[PDB]
Image (cartoon, coloured by chain):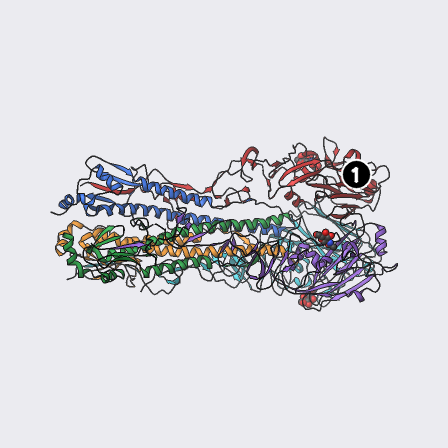
Chain colours: A red, B blue, C green, D purple, E orange, F cyan
């Protein structure tokens, strides 16, 4: 007799999926819901490149460590990259106060301009701005210092009361950093600043702090028994910052006008940076995906798939495959 | 589960390549496979929708996961680790179970379609054909290519063939 | 999907106003709509339960979301923003999918009820009525208002009418 | 031949829902699962009203800024409201130490009473309690000061060592605040307190701190080149607090007996406050709902629906609607 | 729902003890219950899988929940409380709903199996038996223990009995 | 009349277990499994086969400083978490702040190796200062005035307090925890009486740490009979690094320090549940949980590899079918 039969597709396929009732069911068609591929590159995020530090810390880079000016300084970045070899930072030993908060705040800026707040050539006529140099920060073989600060020292036999202000006319906020130096011994204090019993004061509308030298011998670090502490503040548009000192103040030379962004981060990685566009970035490489889940890395930056611990998330689209 | 796929229709057809569900006829003019275009098309639409839903409902914020803490900030460093792990455990569990549940339902969806295609046909032929089982119908009458297609799009004429059929069924 | 709603019964009835599922009779005494009270009532009970479940299982803590952080506390301020965004993303994704999955199942729930109401009837009449399709039965005998209601509550007397029916089934 | 038919309801309805397989399916009946309506008011939470500051900060309110005593001071609140115009705070410039923690701890109190720990009239017979007034804190046109503190100054030519204790007999904890003044110049220090080299000490059973004046000129704020720092501590029942000083201490006058609550918060908003009951409060208005989700505001106080990003969450109750 | 369990087959059998689904015959040689082994076994496999899935997919980190804060750290103490409470609300909600959704589906799964077992039989006998309703078939012919078993494993011989049946019909 | 009968059906039984579904509450089923762990063993156990440190009468503070009441404790070189009791009460017996105390307790949570040693031997370290009269009524031992075991309260010898200077290089290959104190007398008479020099100072230094301390002389309200105070400080000295102390008064000097290897995230539980020889993978303040199950309602604050805490009272999964006898 003539016959009509109802049936369903079967094919080549060897994809398997799991269901709640059965494991390893072969299906005709199927789609993976888990992104497991990255591009092995550090990319631009929302079309703007990261700041890449290479040899240096963030500390090394904003203080202006002598090794850190091989870096072309851009006015914009979407996140910051340090490498495992990012080693040049504070070359004169000391605390960098609220360092982590600085690195957070500096994560991502839409505008960033370096400028000379206190021009070296005309700012300090009663103090020595040239002998402020150390074996702890060497440059072309010679004793050197940070590019963005100046270590003032007495001129002849006098350290007169120093007093100096800056008003923020930049229209953005400006980041200013300074240091205070703690000699090893009384002989060193007197030798560098004359006045035993020196003090420093730094002030703005919101900031106010007095500093006194803590004279003692610490364990040798990069050949120094003294120490320098590093400080920073953000001066608001229209506000003024004033320095007053009778010794021990390592003075600002360059400061930074900037416009902070929002939440970005710092990645530490040896993945090479590329001209390359992404919307989700990890320390291993970028993820270009539509998919809701990834297992590449828990710590991402951008607009990212949710990180999961699974190795496969295969969704059935076709039917059970019965050849 | 609806009992059709790997059920009363025990196997699939590697021969039918242009769709997910269809027919195999055999008459006087020849034999062959033809996919049911309408219900195949409908299914690919709906399954496309399911995939797109699972993907496109994921609202995603621009955020930077990482945070850095100082040697005297282990507590908040650990607080921060607790939130990252907590999210890990909920997203992992949800994603795994979502996939398991939806797969189970997709397979049953297909089963349901096949079963409805079969019933769509039994409904039309009634006792003009013999249900052989295995999803096949044996006609009690000659059914040519035009007849075959009248079945495939729901326009089978039952009265047209009832006499011929009932002769072969009975006497 | 069970193949009834927008299936073999291709349309709904704006005429039936006192329930979700029911009947349309047409005999000698007149015609009209009547909702099936028992299965409608049962369905409104179970759907009420589904809604109440989705609402009432939400355990809710007294909490104050907002926190205030000083200018040297951007890290923890950002930690805090991470947790709020993390919760946003899971509650948004779960709510969306919960709605999607439940809707899909509510519609199939209804399809199932309709299909079972149909089969409850075919089961009773057997070959005393002709399955016309479109969810209609044509009686092979006279079926008055009392007969109609014997069907509606499951107490149809098959033997009572078998002779009358089988006479007409020949003719 | 007569006929029985099986069928299903259809109606007026134009509500649509989405399913995983299909978008925009018209259904007969339907319920929204997402609360999107608020009442545009700030209300009482668990039947007790918030503390509404108006013109002032919390700082200005607990210190007793002269602009802040238009406020009727209740002994109970469920949360605190500041407005975008809440501007009168510390009128003499300085840091308010652990301010944000104070605001957290003061969020919600079940009992709160202001009292005079150190009565002005009898507490300071050897120091001047009347000339401690400034252009930085003006009242009815005149120079004034905070109501809750007194700025003690030398009497004639002497500032004798001051020493004063309070034992907490209130049975609750008491909040005490005090300030320490940093003059602009030596001439001012001596002028106000006589003794160059003054100090202050404050102590309890758990608290101990020495303070020394930091004399220097800061940038002008509200016409001041000196500064004042504000401090606070919670003295436990039975414990004692003692103040010792040879100058620079701005002394407590009023303190606060209180019973802290639990986790409430501060909302900053210009939404008006109403006699009105709620269990969930947002900066935009209150949410009276049975539903599990809301898209009104992420930052709520009380027992709230979960915040989501969606615009509709319509649950089907009826069947597919087919006219 | 498939309409079988507490449906057109209105009750269960306390008498059938060796399986979840099965048969009750009554012929000339005696009567009794026998569980369908194949479909019972299949179901216990799948339901075991369901339980193991719900349990084994739970990835679990070594962690120490508790944190200690000092009297001047109420804010981060409260932050911490917020993350604990947040997790409590999402795990509670998901767990409750998970159980509700899976139970509904497990009951429907069983309904489906029973309905399919019934149709597997109606399919085979056709008009050699009368559908009585309640999931019973009355044979129009003699069906002994060997005939009964031919039905139970899908090898019923329809033509063999058609004449005998049609006479009685 | 009747032809042979074959019927299709399903199991029913004894069972009274009920489950809930989205559509129905309280449905009796044949077979069923609970998904929610609600039993604990009422004991404090070993986590990953290593026992917790149990402090008994003492704080962490009293235990690392070496409060005189705290050396009934056998000091193990390994622990998986720390237990204090509601009676853990002997801590800093001379009143003062313990700086970064909570951080210290976090860091000391769990150590895979821990060894106490004498960095500055009492007998030979301080030949120009008095190391025997550094004892107080605030810290009593066998009825007599005493002090912490792990620190020494150096005082002037005769009429002189010469500038003190003392270093230690970390040769232990692990990090070492060193603690010290600074003392703030009540009055100038006391300061001079104890250390001679009004205007004393203390300095402490490593490669990363540097801090100067000056005495804050004043009378505080009396605690354990004291009007002065002592502050307690600690730091972790990395392998190869050196720590130096310098002082002209007021320094309470280290005597014992601790070589150690920190673990990872453990925690401190405060509880009166007894500690047992007993193995677990999840620990709570009420008792241990030995379970395969994904959820528990015993306690929100657990340590180990745990089921997720939930607020529910039952989570019964149906395995069998609706039960209809
Ligand atoms: C920049 O960092 C480099 C390498 O990280 C330093 O070079 C080392 O200096 C040390 C310490 O003085 C010497 O003993 C070694 O000879 C150098 N080591 C290596 C690995 O090259 C250098 O001191 C840093 N300079 C600045 C200015 O930061
Ligand atoms: C109060 O606040 C106003 C407006 O915000 C400001 O102009 C005024 O000087 C303040 N005065 C005091 C005493 O705080
Ligand atoms: C230890 O604690 C008890 C309990 O109050 C106290 O009386 C005693 O003085 C304490 N001893 C030391 C040395 O702290």
Residue at the left extreme?
A: B171
Question: In the picture, residue F193 is in which quadrant?
Answer: bottom right
Q: Secondary structure at mark 1?
A: loop
Give the answer, above or below, for where F255 lies relative to A118. below
Which quadrant of the frame does ligand 1 lie within?
top right
- Determine if residue B50 is in view: yes
Q: Quadrant of residue A256?
A: top right
Q: Nearer the viewer, residue E110 or F219?
A: E110
Q: Which residue is label 1 attached to?
A: A152
Binning the other alpha carbons within 10 Å of mark 1 as few (below 14), some (14 to 19) or many (20 upward) gives many
The location of residue B40, given as percent across then percent down, is 33, 41
At a point 66% along the width and 37% down the height, the residue shown is A112
- Where residue B27 sits in the image (x, y, percent)? 20, 37
Q: Nearer the viewer, residue E129 or C137?
A: C137
How many marks the image carries: the answer is: 1
Expressed as whole percent of the image width and height from the top left, the position of residue F79 reads: 58, 55
The residue shown at (74%, 32%) is A142
Q: Is residue A181 visible?
A: no
In the drawing, does residue F101 fall left or right of residue F294? right
Residue closest to the far top: A140
- In the picture, residue B134 is in which quadrant? top left
Query: In which quadrant will I find the N terminus of chain D?
Result: bottom left
Q: Measured from the top left, where is residue A150 in percent x and y? A: 76, 37
Respond yes or no on whether mark 1 lies under 8 Å from ligand 1: no
Tell me the chain of label 1: A
Up-down relation of residue A172 to residue E6 (above or below): above
Q: In this orientation, which residue lies closer to the viewer: F239 or B82?
A: B82
């Amino acid at each position: 007799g003539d016959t009509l039969c109802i049936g369903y597709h079967a094919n080549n396929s060897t994809d398997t999926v799991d269901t709640v009732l059965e494991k390893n069911v072969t299906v005709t068609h199927s789609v993976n819901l888990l992104e497991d591929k990255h591009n092995g590159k550090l990319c631009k995020l929302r079309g703007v490149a990261p700041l890449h530090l290479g040899k240096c810390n963030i500390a090394g880079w904003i203080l202006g460590n002598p090794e850190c000016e091989s870096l072309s300084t851009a006015s914009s970045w979407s996140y910051i990259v340090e490498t495992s070899s990012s080693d040049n930072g504070t070359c004169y030993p000391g605390d960098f106060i609220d360092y982590e908060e600085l690195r957070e705040q500096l994560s991502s800026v839409s505008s960033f301009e370096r400028f000379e707040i206190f021009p070296k050539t005309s700012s300090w006529p009663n103090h020595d701005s040239n002998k402020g140099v150390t074996a702890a920060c060497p440059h072309a073989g010679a004793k050197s210092f940070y590019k963005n600060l100046i270590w003032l020292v007495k001129k002849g036999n006098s350290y007169p009361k120093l007093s100096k202000s800056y008003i923020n006319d930049k229209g953005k906020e400006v980041l200013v950093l300074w240091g205070i130096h703690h000699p090893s011994t009384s002989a060193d204090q007197q030798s560098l600043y004359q006045n035993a019993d020196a003090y420093v004061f730094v002030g703005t509308s919101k900031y106010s702090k007095k500093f006194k030298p803590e004279i003692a011998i610490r364990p040798k670090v990069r050949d120094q028994e003294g120490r320098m502490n590093y400080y920073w503040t953000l001066v608001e548009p229209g506000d003024k910052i004033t320095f007053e000192a009778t010794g021990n103040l390592v003075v600002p030379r360059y400061a930074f006008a900037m416009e902070r962004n929002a939440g970005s981060g710092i990645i530490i990685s040896d993945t090479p940076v590329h001209d390359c566009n992404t919307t989700c970035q990890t320390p291993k490489g970028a993820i270009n995906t539509s998919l809701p889940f990834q297992n590449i890395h828990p710590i991402t930056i951008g607009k990212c798939p949710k990180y999961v611990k699974s190795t496969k998330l295969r969704l059935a689209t076709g039917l059970r495959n019965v050849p | 589960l609806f009992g059709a796929i790997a059920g009363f229709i025990e196997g699939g057809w590697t021969g039918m390549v242009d769709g997910w569900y269809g027919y195999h006829h055999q008459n006087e003019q020849g034999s062959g496979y033809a996919a049911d275009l309408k219900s195949t098309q409908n299914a690919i639409d709906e399954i496309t929708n399911k995939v797109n839903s699972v993907i496109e409902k994921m609202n995603t914020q621009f955020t930077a996961v990482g945070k850095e803490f100082n040697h005297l900030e282990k507590r908040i460093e650990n607080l921060n680790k607790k939130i990252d792990d907590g999210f890990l455990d909920i997203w992992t569990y949800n994603a795994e179970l979502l996939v398991l549940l939806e797969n189970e339902r997709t397979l049953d969806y297909h089963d349901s379609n096949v079963k409805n295609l079969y019933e769509k046909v039994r409904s039309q032929l009634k006792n003009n054909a013999k249900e052989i089982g295995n999803g096949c119908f044996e006609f009690y009458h000659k059914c040519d290519n035009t007849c075959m297609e009248s079945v495939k799009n729901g326009t089978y004429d039952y009265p047209k063939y009832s006499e011929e059929a009932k002769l072969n069924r009975e006497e």
